[PDB]
Image: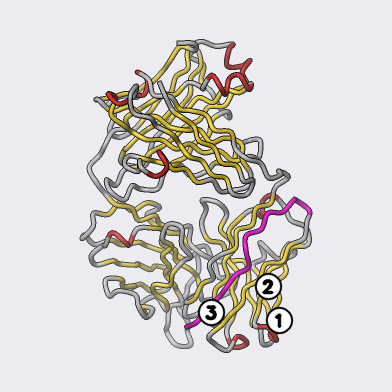
Amino acid sequence: EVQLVQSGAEVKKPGESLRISCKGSGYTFITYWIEWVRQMPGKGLEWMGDILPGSGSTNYSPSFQGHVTISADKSISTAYLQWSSLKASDTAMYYCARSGYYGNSGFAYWGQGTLVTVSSASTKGPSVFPLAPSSKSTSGGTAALGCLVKDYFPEPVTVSWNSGALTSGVHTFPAVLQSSGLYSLSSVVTVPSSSLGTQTYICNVNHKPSNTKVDKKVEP
Amino acid sequence: DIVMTQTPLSLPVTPGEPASISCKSSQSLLSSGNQKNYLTWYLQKPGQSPQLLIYWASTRESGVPDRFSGSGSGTDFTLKISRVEAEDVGVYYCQNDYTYPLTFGQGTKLEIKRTVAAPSVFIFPPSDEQLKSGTASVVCLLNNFYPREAKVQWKVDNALQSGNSQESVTEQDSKDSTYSLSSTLTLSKADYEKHKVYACEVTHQGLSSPVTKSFNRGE
């Protein structure tokens, strides 16, 4: 089977250099084009450029030319995408793909993607605050409650409820990048209003990059 | 660059019904050499790498179900799904594969169409724990609504806010095909305590009139 394996997630400061890699197996690497595609958080796909590893022949989107260099080492079946000086705007998922010339028959095989985060922020564990159920969060016998998971870097956090016992009616929101450059999300759950003063509701928050683990009891 | 424009931007589909996505190129993708249209379709499922569906405008990639078909010529192309499955949800992209640069369309989100559901609107004042630390996050929750489109405006003592709130929306719920939305208003403790009434104004298809969920600070 044909496989493209990309290098691991990167967290970098603005102005730093970076090289990410795409290694091809299960085919003759020199004979197919390696394509590079950018996807900014929550945005569409952007074609960056390509390379034929056998010859080192390249094509660039004029939108990316000058800021990135695409190269290949045919001896180790690897293609590269590199920056001399990263910008915050380089924060994106980067895919490599295998293709013919012009991508004429489409990009048939894709790498798993490399997440690149470019930020002045340092590794930080979140604070966890209750989103307390009240008359302002109750409608029709059901009450909403949650946890606000604020001020962490980098992504991601995971949230469970009652150590995984409560899964029904749970909505954990995608993270947003705050004005501060730190991430935040909320996790919410709808529960019976009658259980508010009797049943215990605890959110369990794990932030692996900082080894922060927080359990917060959510009460009215 | 060749510009690739997709219509529609959002496509609600009832599973089982046909769906069509149009892609318009700003220049012709039809080769004089072989009369092939060099247009490609991809699907990107939530949290996954993109997958090849169709190339040369009408040729299915091996492994792609026969419900997917492509047609069109020159500058106008159509991806058709004859009978939409639940696993077809995600973002569909067309691509110019005729000439460099190999530009993508902006994408079309295929989502499950269901009956309109108005949001259950809830408001959360900041916790005492957070206020003690010096910050006030005020959370407005719009729960279990359809469709995705919603307008949320913050009013503090009847004064419209701007630039101090952020929105997050969940991916379409696997069970009930609804969305949830959070709008979080961030103020410093001092700014928060200057004001009385905190109001979340909500506009949605399921609501006959704009709806205001509010609280008085300290109640």
Other-residue count near label 1 (Cα within 10 Å), few / some / many at <14 / 14–19 / ≥20: some
Residue at which label 3 appears: A99
Residue B130: % across, % down? 57, 24
Instruction: Answer above or below: position of B120 versus A9.
Output: above
The structure residue drawn at horizontal position 31% and vertical position 71%, both measured from the top left corner, is B68
Is disc 1 placed on a helix, strand or loop?
strand
x, y percent for residue A200: 38, 30
Mark earlier in primary sequence (1, 3): 1
Q: Is residue B180 above or below residue B68?
A: above
- The residue lying at 56 percent from left, 58 percent from top is A39
Q: Position of residue B150 (x, y in %)?
A: 39, 35
Q: Quadrant where the C terminus of chain B lies? A: top left
Is A107 situated left or right of A183 in this image? left
**Subunit that carries the residue with mark 2:** A
**Residue extent of the magenta highlight:** A1-15
**Tag 3 or tag 2, which sits nearer the N-term?**
2
Q: Are marks 1 and 2 in contact (CB under 8 Å)?
A: yes
Looking at the image, tell me whether mark 1 or mark 2 is earlier in sequence order. 1
Mark 2–mark 3 distance (CA, rounded to whole Å): 15 Å
Label 1: which residue? A73
Q: Are marks 1 and 3 on the same chain?
A: yes
Residue at which label 2 appears: A80
| In contact (CB < 8 Å): disc 1 and disc 3 | no
Q: Is residue A103 above or below residue B15?
A: below
Label 3 secondary element: strand
The reply to the same-chain question for discs 2 and 3 is yes
